Image 1 (cartoon, protein in one colour):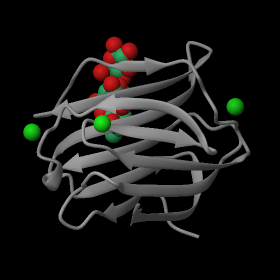
Image 2: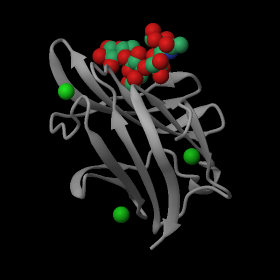
Image 3: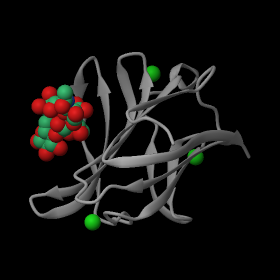
Image 4: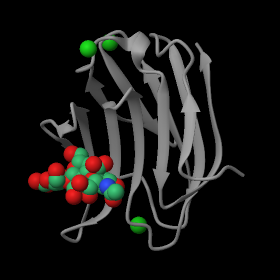
Length: 138
Ligand SMILES: CC(=O)N[C@H]1[C@H]([C@H](O)[C@H](O)CO)O[C@@](O[C@H]2[C@@H](O)[C@@H](CO)O[C@@H](O[C@H]3[C@H](O)[C@@H](O)[C@H](O)O[C@@H]3CO)[C@@H]2O)(C(=O)O)C[C@@H]1O
Ligand SMILES: [Cl-]
Ligand SMILES: [Cl-]
Ligand SMILES: [Cl-]
């Protein structure tokens, strides 16, 4: 088991065909999960499942530049469930991050931060037990 919040270095940044796989279990009565792909203090890609936003379940995606959040992209398809194991896979493609959960396509996020080689850390946080966090090239 791994300690949350967990920082996964991405040596030399991200590159197309890099696949990041996160395995864990959502805690009972969870409120949030967050994956933050960082470029220094900036957040290139914030992936943020929210279990209770005005009694709705929603995934919020955004970018933070110079301490300011941008325009949110929201997804109503919500594959997570409190108490249950999950697999998140983030595939870096030339023009977007592609996210699949439990082997099903979920969403894609167009690159707002364009210096991919400088996105060199992934932060994992929220109401989860974290089992594994790794990457490979496909
Ligand atoms: C230490 C700590 O708990 N930090 C939080 C911060 C702070 O709460 C922040 O200063 C706001 O008080 O917020 C963080 O989550 C934010 C992030 O998920 C962004 C993504 O867009 O959304 C923010 O909420 C939005 C909300 O989605 C909009 O509907 C609303 O109009 O504006 C809100 C504020 O911008 C989240 O607060 C953060 O990472 O900055 C979560 C940290 O845990
Ligand atoms: Cl739930
Ligand atoms: Cl692409
Ligand atoms: Cl950039």
